[PDB]
Image: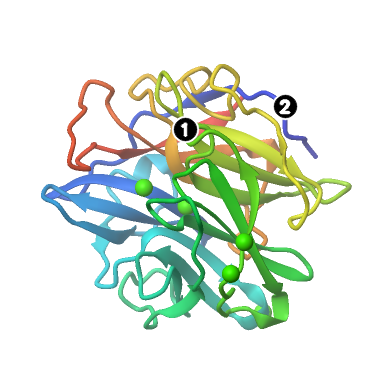
Amino acid sequence: QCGLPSTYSWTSTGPLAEPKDGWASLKDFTAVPYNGQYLVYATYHDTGTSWGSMNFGLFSNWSDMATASQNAMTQSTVAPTLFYFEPKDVWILAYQWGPTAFSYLTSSDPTDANGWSSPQPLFSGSISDSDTGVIDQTVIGDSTTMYLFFAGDNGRIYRASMPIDQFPGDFGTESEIILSDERNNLFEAVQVYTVSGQSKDTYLMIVEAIGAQGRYFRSFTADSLGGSWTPQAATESAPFAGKANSGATWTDDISHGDLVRSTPDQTMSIDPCNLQLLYQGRDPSLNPGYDLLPYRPGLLTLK
Ligand SMILES: [Ca+2]
Ligand SMILES: [Ca+2]
Ligand SMILES: [Ca+2]
Ligand SMILES: [Ca+2]
Ligand SMILES: [Ca+2]
């Protein structure tokens, strides 16, 4: 068994895939182990003004991601969260910019980018002091409760909860603000995981921040998903993952993605002995506007 360190240091792959022809970027990755392989969903931006979602074909090795297929979704599930909700034998794809503040689709075969149900409401509430409104949800459960976490591009991280029996369902309208900092410091792309192999419940939160050298992640930890969060690696010079410690040669940004989860279920479990981050990065010298930033997947592996 292993523990999470209070500071982090990684090595990185190069960019793992080029976007489908006609797309500018692949973003906001969510991944699960599936069939002994990896199943990845993502945001895309085209080479014009439009957003969508996609999945990759199954692939076994991270170096196979470059030749995995890229499958555009008919239902746009921007900034998706993929997981298997084991208690009801159902796969969940949570996302934003759907019919309500957050939405989810259901499926029995998550490999089919276009085999999902029509949307169901995941969250119908709003937040104060945000120009974007709610963004970048994730969903995670323990033995009693399912939790919704999200951001607001406003320095704040939010949480909603429901008894686990009630899921899949709408978390409702209410949320609690659980962290608040400068806007750049707790910006977006929040993720929460159960650290496996621990003698007491241990949860890891990462939040994307805007740094002087680029996008990076700050980490927080908690003893309970419904408890308070304490900063862990939470500065740009000693971050969870960023230019300071990523070993990434092709990107300064370490941005919206997913730690590599050890199982696909709602506990969002990670193996601290084999910590890896599937992130979005981009060539530092290409800085177009219009949301055309050429984000690509990359993989950090914890030393
Ligand atoms: Ca985004
Ligand atoms: Ca089951
Ligand atoms: Ca996400
Ligand atoms: Ca209210
Ligand atoms: Ca509230």
Residue 135: image quadrant is: bottom left
Q: Is residue 36 visible?
A: no
Q: Neighbour class for label 1 at 10 Å: few (<14), some, many (≥20)?
A: some
Residue 138: image quadrant is: bottom right
Q: Amino acid at mark 2?
A: Ser
Q: Is tag 1's residue or tag 2's residue first in the polypeptide sequence?
A: 2
Residue 146: percent from left, percent from top: 67, 68
Q: Nearer the viewer, residue 69 or 6?
A: 6
Is 35 rendered above or below residue 216? below
Q: Nearer the viewer, residue 150 or 278?
A: 150
In the image, what residue occupies the spot 13% across and 49% down?
21
In the image, what residue occupies the spot 56% across and 16% down?
237
How many numbered discs, if any? 2
Mark 1 or mark 2: which is in front?
A: 1
Cα gap from disc 1 to disc 2, whole angstroms: 22 Å
Q: Neighbour class for label 2 at 10 Å: few (<14), some, many (≥20)?
A: some
The residue identified by callout 2 is: 6
- Helix, strand or loop for disc 2: loop
Is 171 rendered above or below residue 22? below
Q: Left of 170 or right of it: where is 280?
A: left
Q: Residue furthest right?
A: 199
Residue 86: percent from left, percent from top: 64, 74
- Helix, strand or loop for disc 1: loop
Q: Amino acid at mark 1?
A: Asn
Quadrant, the N terminus = top right
Q: Left of 204 or right of it: where is 62?
A: left
Q: Which label sits on residue 184?
A: 1
Q: Is residue 76 visible?
A: yes
